[PDB]
Image (tube, coloured by chain):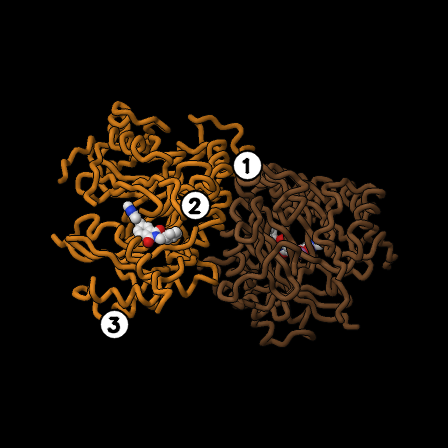
Chain colours: A brown, B orange
Amino acid sequence: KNPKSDKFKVKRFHHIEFWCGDATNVARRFSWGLGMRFSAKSDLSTGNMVHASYLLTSGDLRFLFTAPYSPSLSAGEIKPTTTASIPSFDHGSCRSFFSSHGLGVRAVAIEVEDAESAFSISVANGAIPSSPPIVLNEAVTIAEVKLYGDVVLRYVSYKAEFLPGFERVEDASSFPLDYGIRRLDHAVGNVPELGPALTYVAGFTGFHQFAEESGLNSAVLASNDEMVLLPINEPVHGTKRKSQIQTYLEHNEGAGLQHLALMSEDIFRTLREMRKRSSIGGFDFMPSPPPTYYQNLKKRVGDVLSDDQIKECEELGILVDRDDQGTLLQIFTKPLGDRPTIFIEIIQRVGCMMYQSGGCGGFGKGNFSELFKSIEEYEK
Amino acid sequence: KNPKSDKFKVKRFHHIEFWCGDATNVARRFSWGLGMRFSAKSDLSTGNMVHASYLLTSGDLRFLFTAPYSPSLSAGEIKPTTTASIPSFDHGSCRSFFSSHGLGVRAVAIEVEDAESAFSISVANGAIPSSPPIVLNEAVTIAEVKLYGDVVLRYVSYKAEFLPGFERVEDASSFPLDYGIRRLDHAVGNVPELGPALTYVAGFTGFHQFAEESGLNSAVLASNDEMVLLPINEPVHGTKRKSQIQTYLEHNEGAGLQHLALMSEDIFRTLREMRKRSSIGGFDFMPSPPPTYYQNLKKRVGDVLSDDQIKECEELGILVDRDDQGTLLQIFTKPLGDRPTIFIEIIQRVGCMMYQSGGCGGFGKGNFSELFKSIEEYEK
Ligand SMILES: CC1=NN(C)C(=O)/C1=C(\O)c1ccc2c(c1)C(=O)N(Cc1ccccc1)C2=O
Ligand SMILES: CC1=NN(C)C(=O)/C1=C(\O)c1ccc2c(c1)C(=O)N(Cc1ccccc1)C2=O
Ligand SMILES: [Co+2]
Ligand SMILES: [Co+2]
């Protein structure tokens, strides 16, 4: 059941912003590890004396990396005279975020029809304001409300290239890397208590819960067409193996974004290219499941994937799950930075053609138990 | 003239430590861009609840990348019970350094015969103490004094693998990258006033000045065998083009390390491999000199390099200078991070065989004027 109760018109995920200590080095690492191109910048060379911001793109996926300059460069500025291209940016907030949480996502940005109205409706329905609506060059409006922890939900709306004040980057500096990633599928938060988090966010967006004993309890909030998907996790305390959600909250100093799921148009090619680069600057992957997990694939998805395609899943360490409507291919990276906090998921979905409907195959919940039993091959 | 007046026995450069916000991402970028292998770690997986530290190596060159964890992980610790592997590390100092200066060098480490004696002699001769001598596992002694700005000179001495508490890294995680870089040749500081900086450092080391109108005044301090080379720059104010030394001091919030010069055993191969990677996660290089600069190479170094080797310098943008004893090949990267502060120099020296004596060919001073005149080809 989909009650289509969005309180304002939401389009698609627009971008994800990381707050960094040095945006250059993180952006360059991510570009090589994920196959994203450098497409826009806002920094000293563009007149921005406040923050350095670099945009990576792959298909429709947009990753923004921002770090503060010395406050001394902009000490004579006031908000009415700022050279910052992102008006919500604040030196003190960014340095406090990074010292507290380490490298992580500050903003989950969605494109809406009217960011001014989205903000006003959100706060009238309980959203905690973070940055009021600001009109950039009479062309784009940005506004921010609190989502969970120190993560904000950013509304962006366009009258009619990323943002005013950003520049297209040099062709020579923009190598056309591409490993197949195409869009953000979903973005997952970790909180200490699921109930209050869900009520708060669903309360100000109108997002509805999306149709679904180790580690977590979870639930997914979805927009009207179910293309914006925001799952939220809480720990389950007191078991034998310590909850990875609890470990996250300890090392992150509280609630924050846990993982970003990136859709690939060819997950076999994406993982081939990412795994080739794991030990030469890219990203590492969780340990692969045992061969018994793939011996058990035939009975569950043997009508969807060939034996060769199943053998191909086994080489790359890909996980497979199944809903009533679709099939899910997925895999998880090791943490993206120093702390055991944020990581990335690569996914591809098959089934549910109409365009493909959102969340086709779900989110992999059945893999927890399929892993444990397959990891009970300590007798073979 | 070399008075050989070192006040304690100095061996070689040992390592350079960067203070970072996220050591993982900077270490991975540098590894790919420079061709250095991951060789040691000290982090949560090794029992260190205080800082994450990753060591990259190429030949004898050692780059250390360190970032702080949340202080909450180690809140019950005291210095006598610390899990830190580098006893001088302090959460507050590191976060303050990074917020003030951005990504940069915290420590220039040299190996000595007795770091305890080096520290005591240094401070008896005016060195400002930073971290007292500490004995690690009865095997290694580390001590630190202030060098300039917030950069420290670190003494390391070994009774008889990097440091106790560091672990050798997995073979699968240690890809054997190598672009030819082999050791640190020299490390250069930028200060507001050269005179007082030289007197302070030469005063506590006994290092002697090494035998040598746009931008800077400079001088080089050298150890007894002239294998440890520490140049220092000051700005020249009031000219037409703004001093790059002054720009550094503004963006860095004062004195700090300006550049690291890395010796290559094959500078043609090093620059081939680095330039291939510039736009896919590695490092960018300053713009190459005009063809007239290389047309003028024949008359200055035509007895040292063939026309083909000169043509090869032109393809890679390599600069060439000449002393009375030797010849110098050199090139400079763009800044390593967000701020126009620290950069890297790649160098190879030819001449002065005995082993090669230190500073053979000098440091490239003649290139300033050879560039200006060659850049006066706006008439050809
Ligand atoms: C669940 C779920 N619900 N929702 C909304 C989601 O998006 C979602 C996942 O993405 C998801 C699905 C399957 C697995 C994991 C995550 C996972 O972490 N592991 C094992 C593991 C990997 C790395 C570190 C520690 C433990 C799995 O088997
Ligand atoms: C001098 C000198 N004295 N000592 C001890 C040294 O180590 C030393 C150099 O390394 C050195 C030698 C030649 C050049 C540069 C540095 C340099 O920066 N440029 C142009 C340029 C490059 C990048 C940004 C702005 C301007 C040169 O032509
Ligand atoms: Co997921
Ligand atoms: Co130099």
Image mark 3: chain: B
Q: Nearer the viewer, mark 1 or mark 2?
A: 2
Find out whether the residues at labels 3 and 1 contact each other: C-beta distance under 8 Å: no
Q: Is residue A286 above or below residue A237?
A: below
Q: Is residue A290 left or right of residue B270?
A: right
State whether residue B14 appears in this view: yes
Measured as percent of width and height from the top left, residue B156 is found at 29, 36
Badge number at residue B341: 2
Residue pointed to by mark 3:
B308
CA–CA distance in space, label 1 to label 2:
28 Å
Q: Position of residue B80 (x, y in %)?
A: 42, 26
Q: Quadrant of residue A297?
A: bottom right
B164 or A80: which is nearer to us?
A80
- Mark 2: which amino acid? Thr
- Chain letter belonging to callout 2: B
Residue at coordinates 31% horizontally, 30% vertically from top-left? B196
Find numbered disc 2 in the image and state the secondary structure of the residue it sits on: loop
Mark 1 or mark 2: which comes first in sequence? 1
Does the rendering let one see residue B137? Answer: no
Q: Are marks 3 and 2 in contact (CB under 8 Å)?
A: no
Marks 3 and 1, the one that precedes in the sequence:
1
If the image is split into quadrants, where does the C terminus of chain A sit?
Answer: bottom right
**Ligand 1 occupies quarter:** bottom right
Three-letter amino acid code at the position of disc 1: Ser
Quarter of image, res B73: top right
Label 2 packing within 10 angstroms: few (<14), some (14-19), many (20+):
many
Badge 1: how crowded within 10 Å, few (<14), some, or many (20+)? many
